[PDB]
Length: 100
Length: 100
Image (cartoon, rainbow over all chains, first blue to last red; front, side, top):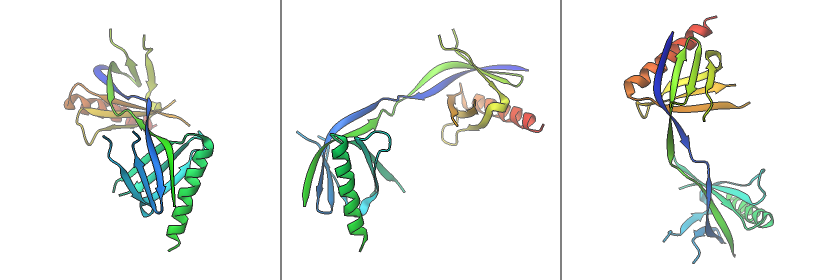
């Protein structure tokens, strides 16, 4: 038995773009600020559910944030050593805050 | 306490492209053939782990296929009624085959 149908394969684009920001840790706040139209993103440490340095690419890390919808922010640090510093700092701020 | 870091937000492109194919059901084989460089994809019904009509868009459906890596083929039928026919047909072929 044999039927043929006209169909479309749906395929997403795989390229990953990278838009420069400044990530600042200011007491218990994290700010994602563009350098010199994008508006500044202000996170409180209490909002961060996850912060993890990539097991694949040393310069990559992500911060998952509750603000039913978790925002997932993936980032690239200037270097693997900076990546470790940002992730460590944020993991320490989160430990410290969560202690209470 | 206050540190600022130069970082990149990593963002994937969200657009979904759609590349025409012909999907043919030929006994227990499904072929994904381009119409008139792409090579024909030949699936046996035993390879299909899932085939489901979208709950969001009537013309959409997907076929998940084992060939540790499952291929996920998302498609758009010419119409919602054709979508239902393709999905029904494939679900029936899978029932029939799996009966053994």
